[PDB]
Length: 99
Length: 99
Image (cartoon, rainbow over all chains, first blue to last red; front, side, top):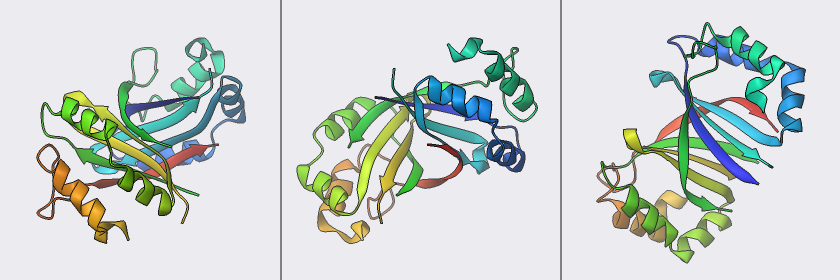
């Protein structure tokens, strides 16, 4: 019901690892995201700037979920992350929408 | 049927003008986009970097359309544009999708 977008940062040269790990995204994480109202979740890359742009829809607390935290730990070597291994994330404000 | 994303550049300090002009997007342009298979077209801003991230769905030649070109001309003072007034646009490759 709501559209959300955000920017993340990949470490230089890690597009391949990022893509392969996401091709093998744990089914537990996919189901948790769905159970929490997430759909149509896409992540796009600007490889030359090591930038990820994420878009998702949310239909109404994953940061405290054990599986999410395990995913952060698994990804922390190739992403720009905080001390708790969650990815740095910059929110992006919607300025236009046409259905 | 296809998801597309791309990055554009706004001139410094022009978020307000960009948003107001898009709130008043010409109905002719909305209809042309729909007629050409575009839906769920969102544009998000990272204001501190003057960056626009666009997402849209396309269900199967707008660059040569007179109304599109008029829109480019109308917007050219506040966007980073080419000599023909079309916005500079960097495509972003999808690296993850979960329906």
